[PDB]
Length: 329
Ligand SMILES: Cc1ccc(N/C=C2\C(=O)CCc3c2oc2c(Cl)c(Cl)c(O)cc32)cc1
Image (cartoon, rainbow, N blue to C red; front, side, top):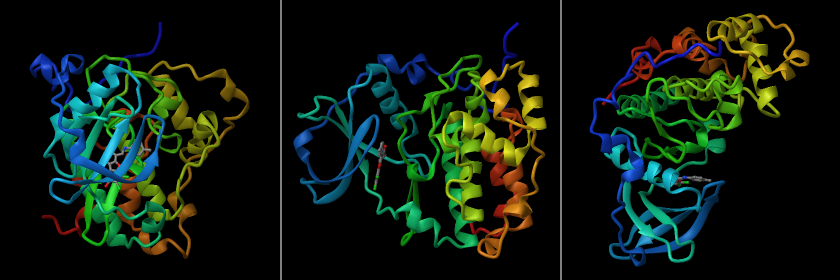
């Protein structure tokens, strides 16, 4: 009969109550700036869909970041632009400051506020228990905001969380995979980085929602408090689900696919095995025990669940006792 449908348990119908133009990004008209306002300083990184540069606004000597988009699809470029404009001003959302036409690539170049980011490989080795809770709360503010605005990020990972640790500033970046949530819509499962893909993606269940980001966030939390980055270190997309199953167990995985009438890829028949769920104390050792608390493990347990409908929402996560000790603004 096919898979059972699913829908978000929060912010379900936010987009159908909005003007069509809010989410119909294919009809958006880009307002262009002057590309010669910015001088490229150095390349910061390259990805599948863009190259990113540190730059200077030569009109005021202000440092910015320029993201030159690769030619991809008028849809995906307009999608990222529309989402960045819809979310601009939200808590810990990276601010899109300008859009110009790059003369070399002949594609849009997005100009962002500059964040003096600490490399996450280096930064995660120094985070205290309080820092992890503090920055997790800051990420949750960004996630609840974009979810409340009908948008899922779909690429939550350490690389996409810029942190100025000297000034304790955090920004959620790279909205190139973000998408508007429409109930009943089937989405491409080829999103997120492998280590942060939710089980819904790994079992090819397309009717997912905001809760995908909360799984990715749980993967980040596990890597931080246990000091193992990434936590689920699969060699490919299939081994990725096996890695998750060796921790969460196979019985809850089969209950998950049974509930949604999902059929597993038969390739898993010879590699999945039979695994009990593990208690989190197995991953606690003398080198990370100062980052682990009963509150942290309860919170992690409520994020890392196979059933996307059972995971904490971002708002619910901010209510968790794990954050009782964090001073809020
Ligand atoms: C490989 C690859 C693909 C896509 C992306 N997209 C990056 C960014 C944005 O989408 C938001 C702005 C922003 C981006 O990267 C930044 C970095 Cl690295 C620093 Cl340091 C910063 O201050 C700001 C940003 C980056 C890298």
